[PDB]
Image (cartoon, rainbow over all chains, first blue to last red; front, side, top):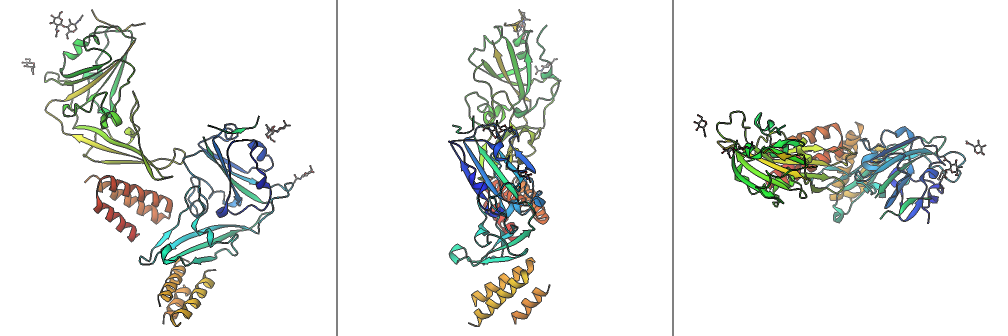
Length: 205
Length: 205
Length: 49
Length: 56
Ligand SMILES: *[C@@H]1O[C@H](CO)[C@@H](O[C@@H]2O[C@H](CO)[C@@H](O)[C@H](O)[C@H]2NC(C)=O)[C@H](O)[C@H]1NC(C)=O
Ligand SMILES: *[C@@H]1O[C@H](CO)[C@@H](O[C@@H]2O[C@H](CO)[C@@H](O)[C@H](O)[C@H]2NC(C)=O)[C@H](O)[C@H]1NC(C)=O
Ligand SMILES: *[C@@H]1O[C@H](CO)[C@@H](O)[C@H](O)[C@H]1NC(C)=O
Ligand SMILES: *[C@@H]1O[C@H](CO)[C@@H](O)[C@H](O)[C@H]1NC(C)=O
């Protein structure tokens, strides 16, 4: 068959802490055609070349996509140390990866803009007997623990969210903090592609 | 021209994990002349006999020399699985080989002893994607990956050495440990001969 | 932002001790929120009595 | 012991990193220290690492 990229071009892309993930196995992909619809502002690959990402055939392909502002290009990197790589979205270093920052051109008219950009500024777990602030750092290929209390979009830059973790969950509290960035004239999106080397996800023709 | 075993007797012998290698092609050798300069304590060959190692013609000869205490004679043996073969020095299993353990004589006043005998007891790689330790074994005719962080001589028995791998290299840590044995009255050395079968390297007659 | 959250937590704690462990936990959460982000500490001290 | 002199330096580096505000590096450095303390069969050093965690 052919790997399907339709869900990317339908609906409103989620936020960085709710990144939407697609898994592709046993299909034929054309990555150059997917990036043709967009205006790629950034393309940085680790453990693989930007030209070689769309040429090789892989055992599995993983594509996370989200709404991301270009003004935070410094935070979305493997060598970065901002809140994006701690509480929002982390990529595994054991596989070849690529980060793409693109812009939804006006002619693509089925990628609806969100109200604004948002991200988890902090996500801590306040323990009980130890009165200790244990930061909750997100691991690779998983969601943040605070996504359950942070809404789909942070209402105001600096909001605080709390959840009373039950004694069984460890008592104490789970606290988060939200931040926002102003929406741009054209929607800007971020993609993260992770490739895993029987190779059945091959380029078409 | 005679094959020159000059670098053996013109400096301090290195350690087992920093073995010094000489390659000989198109020359006449007199192996018994070399061993007559030492006090051979052990001589064991694999895929060849000790009498025929110094009589046949070979396409190429390789000699790896290092410092090695005789109290660890069991670890230096093609069919061992101690830390010496796993992490320090391993010979090829396809070509005829020989291991010689010798003692520097008193009249050999051109060889300087090191402070002590040192080796690598562990060389492992730590992965932060799952927090897993994988030992780093040594391939034939190659140095250990941990030789860049373990110094020329291990200062204390049980030291630990660390090195952080970059996001491109895979992240995590590279960790090694050193072990020491006290110097004896006379420096004791180890040699490893690898012979590959035009057979230009013929013995001097 | 922080001030409204702290005020809401204090208002919740007020109707708990009068209605103790929950009050202490809520006060600890409010103190942590105030410390993480001036007048909030003064409000906490005033509510303590 | 040659293991304590290694864990102490690792803990000092982790403390400096946490003062700098890099939580990922602190989590990585704290992992190496306990890995070394567990490979060297030293429960005391393990307890000292836990106490350092509590104090930070
Ligand atoms: C993969 O996608 C790329 C981009 O859409 C395709 O490239 C175009 O192909 C058409 C038809 O051959 C050409 O007229 C265009 O000039 C090509 N564009 C570029 C930038 O090269 C490519 O053909 C697709 N491959 C497959 C197998 O369908
Ligand atoms: C190679 O070196 C050895 C010494 O290690 C030489 O051996 C001596 O040879 C003479 C002459 O045959 C004998 O009288 C000695 O008894 C030998 N000494 C030993 C220790 O065996 C040998 O001759 C050399 N070979 C060549 C061809 O030069
Ligand atoms: C959209 O496509 C139309 C039709 O080709 C073209 O005229 C127009 O310039 C395009 N707009 C942009 C912003 O590229
Ligand atoms: C070293 O050579 C001298 C030469 O006079 C000799 O007397 C001595 O015994 C030799 N030492 C040995 C063989 O250990």
